[PDB]
Amino acid sequence: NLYFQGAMASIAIEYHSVVLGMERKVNVIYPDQSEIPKKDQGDKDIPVLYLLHGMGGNENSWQKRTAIERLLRHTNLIVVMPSTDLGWYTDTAYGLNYYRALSQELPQVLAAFFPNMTQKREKTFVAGLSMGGYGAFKWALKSNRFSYAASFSGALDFSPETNLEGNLGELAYWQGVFGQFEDPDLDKHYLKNMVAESDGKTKFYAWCGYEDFLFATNEKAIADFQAQGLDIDYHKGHGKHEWYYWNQQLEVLLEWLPINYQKEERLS
Amino acid sequence: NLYFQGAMASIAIEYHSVVLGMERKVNVIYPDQSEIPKKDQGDKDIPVLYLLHGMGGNENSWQKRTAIERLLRHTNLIVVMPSTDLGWYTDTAYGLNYYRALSQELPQVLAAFFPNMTQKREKTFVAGLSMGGYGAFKWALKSNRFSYAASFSGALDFSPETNLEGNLGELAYWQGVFGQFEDPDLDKHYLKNMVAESDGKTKFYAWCGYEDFLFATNEKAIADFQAQGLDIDYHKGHGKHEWYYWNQQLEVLLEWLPINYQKEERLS
Amino acid sequence: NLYFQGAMASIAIEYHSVVLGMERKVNVIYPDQSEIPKKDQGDKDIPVLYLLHGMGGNENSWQKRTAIERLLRHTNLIVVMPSTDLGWYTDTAYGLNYYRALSQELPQVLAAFFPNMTQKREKTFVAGLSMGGYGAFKWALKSNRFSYAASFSGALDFSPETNLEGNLGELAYWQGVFGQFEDPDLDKHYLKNMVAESDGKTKFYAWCGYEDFLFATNEKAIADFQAQGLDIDYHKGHGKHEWYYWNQQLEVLLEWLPINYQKEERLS
Amino acid sequence: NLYFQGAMASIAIEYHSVVLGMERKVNVIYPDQSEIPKKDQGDKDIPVLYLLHGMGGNENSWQKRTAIERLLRHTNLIVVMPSTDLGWYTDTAYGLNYYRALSQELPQVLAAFFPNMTQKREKTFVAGLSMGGYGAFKWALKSNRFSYAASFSGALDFSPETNLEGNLGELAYWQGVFGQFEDPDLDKHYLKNMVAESDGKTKFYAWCGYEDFLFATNEKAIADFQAQGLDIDYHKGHGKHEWYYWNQQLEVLLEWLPINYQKEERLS
Ligand SMILES: O=C([O-])C(=O)[O-]
Ligand SMILES: O=C([O-])C(=O)[O-]
Ligand SMILES: O=C([O-])C(=O)[O-]
Ligand SMILES: O=C([O-])C(=O)[O-]
Ligand SMILES: [Zn+2]
Ligand SMILES: [Zn+2]
Ligand SMILES: [Zn+2]
Ligand SMILES: [Zn+2]
């Protein structure tokens, strides 16, 4: 017609997690064969971005707060939106092994459903905002699964002192996630303590807004990462802890990744 | 926490349409009691915008192609996203009474589920893009239900000559929607022929991009509407038949409507 | 725990149909690796049942009206639930090519998403109820894609005389689906006229309740099929045009198909 | 047509929980105005059943494992399916206040969306299976909101000794839900300790299968309830910890409740 136009496929999966012992939800956007560049048709090695949500969000957050499905509609990229509830992408002290579920089970589930997604590091990426920025860097440092990793307004440094002081949720919550604050192993949850064992083959990007409550956290964390020689680029701009800025950062991410992003025309 | 933030409620309804004789889907976004201005808490007369999709879309289109759920999250507005398949919001010649289903049944269904939505014209609005711009103006002209109506890149004028010539879909399709092209009643589907009987108490807005295939259609249609004294404001800018521009127009619409839109802060 | 138990994966897909020129929905239930018999783990040739809905239904009908997701949870079977609106799995006279979309596009879409589903006739099955029984037999007769095909209370014979006489919907509806009733090609829609060209390598099953308004239709249709030597088994019982009986027939179907159905224990 | 038939409306709601500080999902089935008995049309006091899931389930469990949407389609009943993750409908020791969210917030959310649901005890009911049987009895004992409450294979008695011994999940899990096992307040989670303060105006029903791992638990719990004079009827049959039996018990529940259940005809 001229009236007709493509769309990515939108897939919502509910599956049984053996790790968590419960039904879990994951959303997947999958490229539109009729709209990607000609060369990409039939691909058996499609690149994949895992995009992680913030505290209070879920598998719908990115899709509803950005117009990601519109942005990517001409691009050869699978995007996976997992859920972690309020568990920080962490195996918690109350027995929910969210990190194991994210890092070990989810990729196996997806591969089993979707053999044509890439299994290559050079085509596997992660990013997230807020709690999801912590999750993205944690997963990339520990797993060496990703070529590129990004944090937007991430909680990239913390301590008991900062978590609680009880402006950021109460003690029982934080100790449920990370263990008791007197446990000498608490520090294993600190991203700075995970750099040494990572392989140094992941590119990192971090952003934070000047006005964000986590701006000081990011300044401190990046300084510590840079001291250890992490391959990181850090940027800042005016902004707060809000989804408009996360949308902007998604659009920066899409150009940074090696995905041949087909940016929509904008005449106004 | 400072980490926590609200969200609108997102409601997906599947219901039995007696008019269409089938299960139908409608999405509704409903304002977050914890985030709207104080005065709006407990409202029993909440304003409502019906937002109509384009050819090939459905009840998910606006939500996935704009970040409407983010934009409206501090605003006291219900938004309803109906579906019409490829039926043009029209009672078709193949027996699917989509116009009756939209104009008569859907509002009764919604009121029955949601008694706290407004029943007032001064708080009831419609808009749509492409086919949905035709639908929005048709519904507003015929029903007098709305105070404000908006069309974005709408198919606001047409004839056999323009539909088909077969660049815009084939004959059987168009005649299925509007009837045989030799029927002397074809012209009842033309928006210009619906102005006389409307009550003149609806404000109209139309937009079209210069580069759009429907730019000439809109120029012609608005000239005809203005000749009949319709209360319409018409604007144009650079743009094509694409969702980025429809997102921009949604943001213009939200300020135009009498809804006390709480626009998100944008520091960059 | 003993408290934990598996579930099939439930997948909801929205995809762009090039054939129909619109976003379409298809549901897929996919076997639980942790619950199927040991031997089936890792299968790259998983059997597939397409299950078609009735007039007024959609891709959710089977899942919500039967407890299919519970019944199949130990069985190595993919089940696909397509949607055809009110189009009878037919390329209609108003330009919606539902048959092409079902028979050609949908299998290619699914294979592209899900390479581990079978591509073998011996592991590919179809069934449906009411309109979906017509669709199941039509698709199996025309395509030779299936080893087994089943109709439950199907509209397996019809004419203008029976459609309309206007007890079963009005003329414009029926002629929109099948063309004008005076067209000499109307009879190409009759299943009896499709037997000659089918390959005779599909097993057919049909059921109808004695009290159903289509009981006479089924008696006539099966007699005509049996006259042509179709490989069909036909059964009847007390019942009407209702989902309880369709649930019962699903359970009969699951034993008939060569799928090694792992029937749940029922101690009461 | 005779081909057309009604359906209940199926509503999926995602809403912001202030209590939990996260987006939460609740499903609602709402009666079909065209199919309920004549007298019920226009009701502003529609009865409501809350139906709670088991460990590992969610808001979709009842709908997918029973054909509840089919069973209730002629009946004037709203059914609400909440989610509690693995939190036992309890304000947990890791800071997720699931009980407050269920008992205080959810009813206010639903009333705000759906003013025509009843606010009367005589028309408000709860039931659940496994963990959800514990939840149903807990909520009914504490709140006095319900006239009728039902448990199917519920975990109605427990201790450290039985939880763990580590056949039923590990220590960290159970202590995350209920607190440390040495806390003298552990016993506040025991349903037997909640009877004294309840008002004695709720009717209780419990079922358990003989072969279920919780059969001894139910025998013990009911004996303790009967010693305290609770108004309870307890039944047992052959069965295990499986959804087929929960489906059977749902069908018993529907006749027990004062809802004028319109049971589907079953001629076979
Ligand atoms: O966004 C813009 O300014 C553009 O690219 O036209
Ligand atoms: O969008 C902008 O330029 C703004 O408002 O900062
Ligand atoms: O359904 C039955 O009767 C059984 O198998 O126990
Ligand atoms: O289920 C049955 O046996 C019946 O009621 O026909
Ligand atoms: Zn830089
Ligand atoms: Zn103007
Ligand atoms: Zn037989
Ligand atoms: Zn009894």
Image (cartoon, coloured by chain):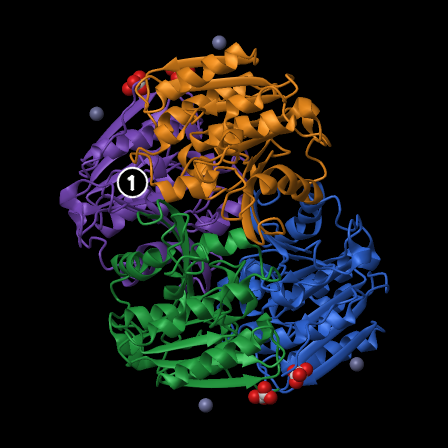
Chain colours: A blue, B green, C orange, D purple
Given residues B95 and D59, the one toward you in this image is B95
**Residue A114, how many percent across, how many down?**
70, 45
**Residue D2, how many percent across, how many down?**
31, 33
Given residues B266 and C103, the one toward you in this image is C103
**Residue A75, how many percent across, how many down?**
72, 62
Given residues D178 and A25, the one toward you in this image is A25
Given residues B7 and D168, the one toward you in this image is B7
Q: Is B200 situated above or below D148?
A: below
The quadrant in which residue C75 appears is top right
Q: Is D149 situated above or below B98?
A: above
Q: Amino acid at mark 1?
A: Lys
Query: Image point 46% across, 12% down: which residue?
Result: C223
In the rendered structure, the answer to whether residue D72 lies left or right of residue D185 reads left
Q: Give the labeled residue for mark 1.
A: D192
Q: Is C209 situated above or below A52?
A: above
Q: Secondary structure at mark 1?
A: helix
Q: How many labels sit on residues? A: 1
Q: Quadrant of the C terminus of chain C?
A: top left
Query: Image point 56% across, 28% down: which residue?
Result: C126
**Residue A145, how many percent across, how many down?**
79, 56
Q: Residues within 10 Å of mark 1 (few under 14, many from 20)?
A: many
Look at the image and tell me whether residue C251 can be seen: yes
- Outermost residue, left side: D39
The quadrant in which residue A187 appears is bottom right
Query: Image point 28% across, 68% down: which residue?
Result: B117
